[PDB]
Every structure is written in C-alpha cells, then in structure tokens.
Image: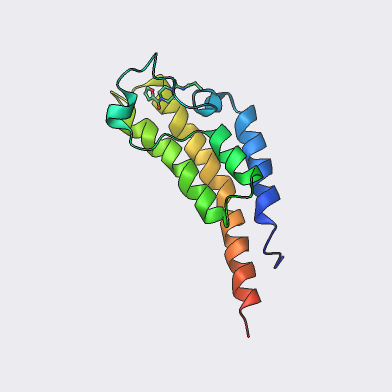
Amino acid sequence: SYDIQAWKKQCEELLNLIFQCEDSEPFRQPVDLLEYPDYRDIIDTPMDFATVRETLEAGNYESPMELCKDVRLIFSNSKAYTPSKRSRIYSMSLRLSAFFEEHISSVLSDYKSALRFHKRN
Ligand SMILES: CCCNC(=O)N1CCN(C(=O)c2ccco2)CC1
C-alpha cells in the first residue's frame, strides 16, 4: 500500500463514477458564456470535470492534492455564481461535492503515507 503512483488510476476511477452521477451534468464541460453572459465578471478561473480528466491524462498533475484543488474550484465557482442556496445547479454541486470528498480522502491519505514511507530513511 506504499505505491506512490497508485493515486492516478484511483482518480481516473473516481472521475468515471462522477461522470455516471446525474448530479455532474452541469459540470462536465466549461460553462457556456452565450447562456450565462456575466460568468467571467464573477468567476476568475473556470474549471470543469473534462478539463480535470484531460489534465490527469496529459500527465500534468504531480499529486492528487493538485487534482483535488481543481475539483474543489468547480464547487467554489458554483457557490460564487449561484443567486441563491435554493438553486437547482448549486444544489447538485453540494451533493456531488459530498460524494467527491467521501471518496478522495483515502486517495490522499494513501498517497501521503506512501511518500512518508519513501523518505523513512
Ligand atoms: C455542462 C453544461 C455547462 N454548465 C453550465 O452552463 N453551468 C454550470 C455551472 N454553473 C453554475 O455553477 C451555477 C450555479 C447556479 C447557476 O449556475 C453555471 C451553469
């Protein structure tokens, strides 16, 4: 269980589960500005799950903490852009965030444990 590289395939599997969740539908592609004309007046750094998957598959994440920061940005952008807490799309973001956090905690713990074991001497 001290495999330093194991997080990558664990993150690919978790992204597959997020793409099967109906709650991911608003977050699978960059927000469309035609529909939401004020989006970049509110959101400095757009993020979505296809961008996360492509960054992972390009080999452009060094750690699962970096992937986790980008996924958390999807959720903080939804909270910043929502006009109410009683919003459909923001409500979907909260359920999807709880699912993501429940599954990513072991991926982070195992990676950090593997790196500590690598430095143990
Ligand atoms: C994949 C389809 C493109 N997604 C898309 O247009 N949006 C998802 C992100 N948005 C929000 O987080 C939000 C919160 C409240 C209202 O929208 C804006 C709309």
